Image (cartoon, rainbow, N blue to C red):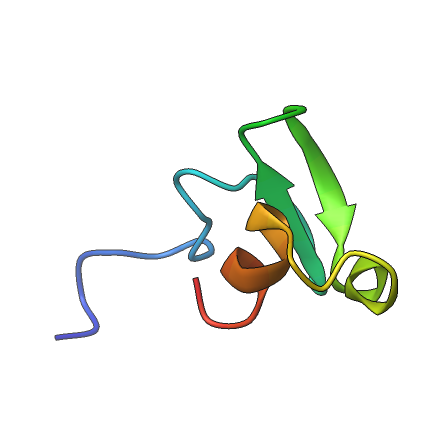
Length: 50
């Protein structure tokens, strides 16, 4: 099932790059590294395996 779709597999509810999580709270692409200070954040838990 290769013939058909191409380009690049982009996100849908988190338009960010490698190693980032989009939070609906503040509305922005946060960094997974932020967890170091905010381990209990929406984007934190959403980052690893959305």
